[PDB]
Image (cartoon, coloured by chain):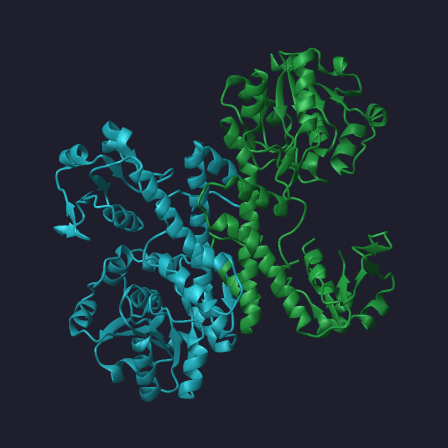
Chain colours: A green, B cyan
Amino acid sequence: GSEFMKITISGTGYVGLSNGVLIAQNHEVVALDIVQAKVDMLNQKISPIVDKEIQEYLAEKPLNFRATTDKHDAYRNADYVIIATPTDYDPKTNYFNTSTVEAVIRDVTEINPNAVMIIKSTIPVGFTRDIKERLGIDNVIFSPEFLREGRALYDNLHPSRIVIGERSARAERFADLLKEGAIKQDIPTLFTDSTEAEAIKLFANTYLALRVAYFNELDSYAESQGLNSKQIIEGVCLDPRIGNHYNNPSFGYGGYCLPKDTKQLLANYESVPNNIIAAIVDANRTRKDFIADSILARKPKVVGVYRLSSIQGIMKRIKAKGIPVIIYEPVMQEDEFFNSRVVRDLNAFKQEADVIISNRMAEELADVADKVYTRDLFG
Amino acid sequence: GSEFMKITISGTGYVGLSNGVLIAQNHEVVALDIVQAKVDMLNQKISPIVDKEIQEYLAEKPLNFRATTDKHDAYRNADYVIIATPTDYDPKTNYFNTSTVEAVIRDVTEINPNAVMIIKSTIPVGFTRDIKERLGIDNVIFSPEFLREGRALYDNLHPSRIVIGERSARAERFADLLKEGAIKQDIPTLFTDSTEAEAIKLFANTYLALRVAYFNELDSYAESQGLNSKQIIEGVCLDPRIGNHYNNPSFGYGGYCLPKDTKQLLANYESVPNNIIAAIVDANRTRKDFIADSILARKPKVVGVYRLSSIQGIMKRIKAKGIPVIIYEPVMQEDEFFNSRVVRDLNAFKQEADVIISNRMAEELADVADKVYTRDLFG
């Protein structure tokens, strides 16, 4: 009887907490965290992370939810344990650090070997099949998370889809828990085998990077041929097989996931003949070179950056010519960024900057649009 | 008064005829063709091409439509002349043959210099701006056609969008004629400058080839890693920013347009730094090598092809090893195809073929599925 289940969350970042609040609406949830201070705020119904819906739900809804720093208390009697501890992939060494996930698997296997673990942390392709065989256990299943930090609970209440990397009754029972707490009805739900589930996000994220890189190359062509990029892009994207989003020219795809995931996938293609996977990584370098070359042809003595991640690679190329960069970014409280000077006064910024670069056009820049370079079209 | 206009169509293939029938529903249309026999069937309301809606409209609706082999009769007093004569791009020489279009432009400029010409034939990027300057004329505008042969009138009655490569009142007046005859309401309509309009289809078609090549590389990876490709693809495509069509693995993108358009665009990128555009062309060669290598590892003495265009590149690679290929394709009335033997008997085909390859799985192949190799998932 799923109605009487206990679900434990191990890791209280946005993924763990989102899943915990979602499920606690209808079931008993216990969140384990190593930091006593976070357990205290949670038990006082205060969210330790910035997320509107999570704070609203914890303070205003009757959730059968509590936290603890105690492992035995957290895991015992758990039907499912959702693992959402920190992990990190480093492209330079091709090293994926999964130590927090393996430590949790260790603890649960010792404390409650009957619990079914659902890993939501990001792990390498093949991780789950491998750890099951290494430890001689079977109670571990991977399920990707498609949440955006800052709208994590919102995304679990309105998910694109639910994917559980096991084809069985207990996987179907866990998918039911996720849909029961959701606001969206009829959520597409897919059951796959293990390694296939772990590859979905890399292929999905790499496709998005590909799309951005493609529209960026279309933009490189338009600039070099003196054409209106927006006219071409809008005409192309009115084809419904292509669609009209994720098509805004930029200085390169960036953010915390695409650069790393594209490289992670390329590393997984080590012995698979391919041209597109490798080109998606190379394309971003080529685009930043093009953007930097276009700015440098203007012969600036100083380049100003209006607001602050691909623009960092543009800064790097400019500073390699001995050209200083000044930055205007109020959100930044630092004195410098990658050694370059943050300027608080906006009117001095416009005066000194021979070329102002930005991933978005802006109202205040109108007066100096003649020296503003942005390829943004739809921001 | 658009209500009293005359529109002439020069070229009666599916694009010319589709536009002519569409417009003749509300206006006077005259179709010029050089072949007297086609003018006769048209005047007898018989369609010279295979297209259900065109034949239905010509035989059953009261269209103010007639044909003629006479140029003076066709062009005089025309407000617009739609040019839809044959053109062809050859990737090997990078030669785009636009002679039929230039001959029409010549004739109209002589016979009725006030007519506004709308080119619907496919032409090279920059063609219209160039011909206007070369001839010292201004009455030529390009508008892409997004029609599928066989559903050409259907596609003009339900278009994805309308793009006219001129931003002016007379371009808006011509777009109105296309929407007036359409069944679909609210058709997205975009007015661009000339060269931008001519680039839309190359970029759109190349994006589709890119998408097919990407899912094909995902499939290469799945096969080589022993994974279920459908599980990964369905999980990826449930992301609404990616969507779920144009994602069926194959032996390579093919057809009459993608192979040529990808190469045509790559040629246009001669002096523009890029990695994706070039990789889209290379990716197809790499995919066919992978597919052929997978078939050859099975050590077939004879490879059978079940139904018949990327599979042609697979045939080529197989025959290069001295391995004969036999083909089962009823639609083909030829004795051979690229020198290989067409077999009419289906049961002999299954007996001789050590490996049966096909871009689609089939009912009759169930009994020999153990030796059938197709990467199709959604056909």
Q: Position of residue A12 (x, y in %)?
A: 75, 28
Position in image of residue B114 (x %, y %) = 39, 86
Q: Residue B349 vs residue A132: left or right? A: left
Q: Position of residue A99 (x, y in %)?
A: 68, 28
> Does residue B267 lie above or below B75 as drawn?
above
Position of the N terminus of chain A, as image quadrant, is top right
Q: Residue at x 71, y 56 (%)?
A: A312
Residue at 82% over, 26% down: A35
Return the residue nearer the eye: B4 or A311: A311
**Is B85 situated above or below B208?**
below
Q: Residue at x 56, y 40 (%)?
A: A202
Which residue is painted at 72% across and 60% down in the image?
Answer: A315
Say above or below: B371 vs B283: above
**In which quadrant of the rendered image does the C terminus of chain A lie?**
bottom right
Q: Quadrant of residue B48?
A: bottom left
> Image check: B33 left or right of B141?
left
Residue B142 x %, y %: 42, 73
Pick the residue in front: B341 or B113: B341
Query: Is B274 in front, or is B28?
Result: B274
**Taking the image as drawn, is residue A116 in sight?**
yes
Q: Quadrant of residue A357?
A: bottom right
Numbered disc total? 0
Work out whether residue B160 can be spotted.
Answer: no
